[PDB]
Each structure stands twice: as structure tokens, then as C-alpha cells.
Amino acid sequence: QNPLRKACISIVEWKPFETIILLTIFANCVALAVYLPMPEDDNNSLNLGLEKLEYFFLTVF
Amino acid sequence: RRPWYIQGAASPKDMLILVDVSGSVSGLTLKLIRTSVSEMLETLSDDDFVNVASFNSNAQDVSCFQHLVQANVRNKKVLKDAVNNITAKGITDYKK
């Protein structure tokens, strides 16, 4: 349907990309295993350093 | 714990019990903190001065006092009745 004016990226999808994504989704799963939930809105330093680092994982995917 | 012993074992004090009412102390820690603060006040005589602060991202007094009071039976009663109403919610900030 769409012509080849948009496909500035179709060439890179067939690179060893699935490895860069399969080892990016692993750090995102480990950044959920070290998150420590605290009662009644409390928080510590590391949990604040992982809510920012979630925008870095929400932008690659 | 007797009055005569606690008297002859030290000199008069200016205690400032600084309870932590952060969110993480909720549960059993908060109950033990209430009972501990009460049993600690019970070790004060009439020459000692005391006040009970409380901090969770904000440091406020726990009662109507706002400065060191004389720790007699009535003031200790006020402080105990005000500590038994403490609730736990917020973040911790030791500097405040």
C-alpha cells in the first residue's frame, strides 16, 4: 500500500537486532526484580533510580 | 525502673523522643514503637523534661506542646494519649 519513501529503517530490521532487543528486555525484567515495594507510599533511593530508568526502557520498545 | 533507682543512677535529662511515622514503619513496627515510647516515658521523673516529635518527610510535634515540658504525671499522660494516635504514611527524611 505505502511506497518505499518511508522505509528508511526496513534495512536495519534484518540486522542482528533481535539480539539487541532480547538483551534489552532482559535488563527491563531485571529492573523489575530489584524493585522493592514499600508500604503506604514510602520509597527509598534505589526505587527512585528505577522509575527514571523506566523512561529509557519505554523509549527503546 | 523504680523512681529511687532511676534517680540515683543519673542526672536530670532533656529527652526528645523522635518517633518515625514514615510509611515503612506501618504494621507491627508501629505498634511496637507506640508501646516502646510509652514504656520509655514511664522512666522519667519530674526534674526531667521531654517532648515527642515525629517525622515523615516533615517533622512535626505529636501533641499540643511544641517545646520541652516538665514530664509530670499530667504531661506524660498527654504525651502517651497523643502517641497512641500516631499513624504511618509517607516518605522518610532524617535530615528534617
Image: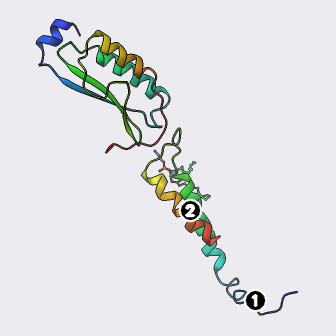
C-alpha distance separating marks 2 and 1: 29 Å
Locate residue A54, reporting x and y percent.
Answer: 56, 62
Chain under numbered label 1: A
Residue B78 sits in quarter: top left
Locate residue B43, reporting x and y percent.
Answer: 25, 15
Residue B76 sits in quarter: top left
Disc number at residue A54? Answer: 2
Locate residue B63, reporting x and y percent.
Answer: 37, 24
Relative horizontal placement of residue A52, taking residue A5 as reference (left or right): left
Relative horizontal placement of residue A29, taking residue A34 as reference (left or right): right
For the point 64% across and 79% down, the residue is: A17
For the point 63% across and 69% down, the residue is: A22
Tag 2's secondary structure?
A: helix
Q: Could you tell me how many numbered marks the image carries?
A: 2
- Pick the residue in front: A12 or B29: B29
- Pick the residue in front: A21 or B26: B26
Tag 1's secondary structure?
A: loop
Q: Is residue B96 above or below residue B33?
A: below
Residue under label 1, please give it. Answer: A6
Relative horizontal placement of residue B52, taking residue A53 as reference (left or right): left
Chain under numbered label 2: A
Q: Amino acid at mark 1?
A: Lys
Tag 2 near tag 1, CB within 8 Å: no
